[PDB]
Image 1: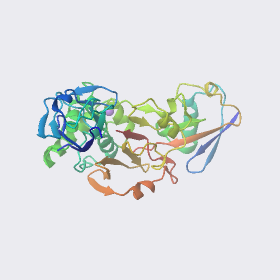
Image 2: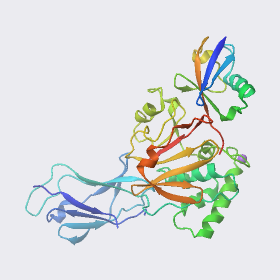
Image 3: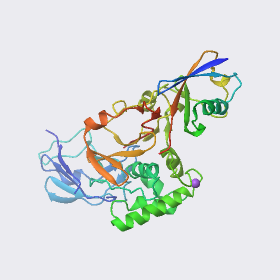
Image 4: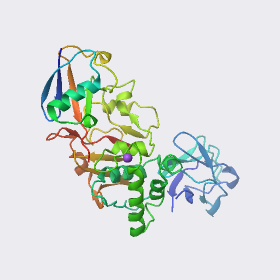
Length: 75
Length: 295
Ligand code: NA
């Protein structure tokens, strides 16, 4: 299924995922596309931070859902 | 009229407090003034010195907590010499936090702004004394936080180098290079309320507003990211971190004045400057404010 990840730079990332994908898996796909390490990513659905050992299904993320990506760059 | 408090003076952990009443007081009618912490805990006071027939000075029997608000409470039943009795307690409030400007913490190793910023927030927090007595926090960090205001330039810089090394040797903090302020807070064992974990909110601001009473430190891990204007309860806000995504500074408040501290550089800043701060950097997508400290 297809999900959309919207960033605060105003980019939409389209991902091909499955309901059983872990959050860590989704961050890995973002890392592949965008070169952002997982530990500098926060993913959000319906106001909630997605946690690394849960699945998309755990949060009721379904086809065509939109997530937000907030970066946490090191300083 | 019944007695009223018309002045309060705190001229430390065991301050002398002066209260002045509108009229002479029957001295026998004020035996158990207390100071109350935000959770209702009462600290008794020692003898009352009668500076005049209507002005008293006293000190708490036990040391008060750092960076904490206390209510001075004069129970109902205080009586004027003219005979009128109060039917409700008389109260006044103060804070134990210092009023001198805060100090810079130089970027000694070149990649420590996240550590310096977190230490600035911790040293302004109501949790400070809990950090200072926490044996899981490295001793060098506790040493630095305990004498931040008093240390000489040389002592502060030595203590800061020792604290940074001790933090870098913890599992939470990177052994070298840049980091995130949360990592340092985890090493300091500072309890944070994660806004995302709120059972009664789906965004950052509402999570803070509807948190359990007396929650003092927040980690802003919901959405959208907050600007300064969006932080609730500005009257009680005393510190927050500010990242550009690549660098951190601290904003800390003492005596009603906000300071921006960029490593060694301390500047006094205006409310207008805080109101102009964005919630995130639109150029890189990185969040501005993740830690908010309230008194
Ligand atoms: Na480390």
